[PDB]
Amino acid sequence: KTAQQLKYIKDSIKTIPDYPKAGILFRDVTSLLENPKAYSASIELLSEHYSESGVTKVVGTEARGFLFGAPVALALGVGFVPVRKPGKLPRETISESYELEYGTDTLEIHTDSIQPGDKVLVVDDLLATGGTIEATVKLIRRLGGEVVHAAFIINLPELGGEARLTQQGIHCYSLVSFD
Amino acid sequence: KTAQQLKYIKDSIKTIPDYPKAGILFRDVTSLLENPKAYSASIELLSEHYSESGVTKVVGTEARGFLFGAPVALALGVGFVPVRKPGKLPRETISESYELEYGTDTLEIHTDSIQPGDKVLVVDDLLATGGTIEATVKLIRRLGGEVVHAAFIINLPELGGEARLTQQGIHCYSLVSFD
Ligand SMILES: Nc1ncnc2c1ncn2[C@@H]1O[C@H](COP(=O)(O)O)[C@@H](O)[C@H]1O
Ligand SMILES: Nc1ncnc2c1ncn2[C@@H]1O[C@H](COP(=O)(O)O)[C@@H](O)[C@H]1O
Ligand SMILES: [Cl-]
Ligand SMILES: [Cl-]
Ligand code: NA
Ligand code: NA
Ligand code: NA
Ligand code: NA
Image (tube, rainbow over all chains, first blue to last red; front, side, top):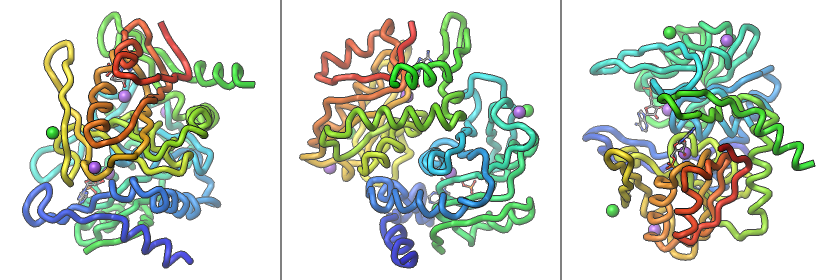
């Protein structure tokens, strides 16, 4: 039933060793996207999960996050709001910066697209360190939105992101997990 | 019926003057994405249009193209294949470079994701000069795929892209047009 669907999704994901550099096992969701069965099931399962949750908006980060969050938004009948790298959004934004191993990056959101009252689901392709999602959550909360759920296709629990998101009050759901 | 749906889509799109620089009228699809009615109708109309076309794959370019092509792919029950900026795809790629006003850029696709026989629909947010779509088409055709249709939310016919795509043998369909 679901174990079989979850397995077919997991099997559809390819692993590319040593990309982008030696040691990393890259989990490639493009092999899932190209399999209509695996892709459609992914969206079904993520949106099923929040069907009674009261969600009013879905937020996904650029660019692979768009591929899972916008279809979940359409499946729930709610608007989709992107969080982008800087200088890509044309109306008024706020921004949040997040530490990387070396250096910092920044994400932005349209100030008009979240307002007090909104219940927001974050959806992304993959949870690693959690830094992007932590910055996204702070963006949505600055704008009065309530977020307590982030959903992913893939969780890499060894990298600590779930743990970090837990400390921000976010519950994470992932379809599959790799070690 | 449809004139009313097309109008509601057009009205949902905001225009930001002088972004990213003076003179440009930026057409912002994020106001459409945040309106579940306008977003859902957009995808309905694009996928309706190709419902009897024999499509086996949809190709969309990063990043806003993902927001329209992947939902069309799911609506047609076909796989979605991204075309990306360089160094973002992990398996074997080919690439195409395209002239910009100043300088050049490049797009890549996974060689395994298109093969002879595939009938490919390209879907993007907006048609301006046509340079990205021309490079995408050459990528898909190098891999044995047949493409004669590109679909957009928005066409800016003054910028010449439709004309250029016509000369590559591509038929373009857009929901709306601005001047
Ligand atoms: N091993 C990996 N395989 C594929 N993508 C990854 C991997 N590690 C990190 N990523 C990507 O990096 C993004 C940012 O992750 P985070 O460190 O959770 O902010 C994720 O959403 C993935 O797109
Ligand atoms: N006036 C505009 N408003 C919004 N986006 C634009 C505009 N002009 C160009 N673009 C974007 O530039 C991308 C590349 O367009 P092209 O020149 O057709 O390769 C489009 O797919 C749009 O995302
Ligand atoms: Cl800010
Ligand atoms: Cl090449
Ligand atoms: Na991501
Ligand atoms: Na707001
Ligand atoms: Na585009
Ligand atoms: Na191929």
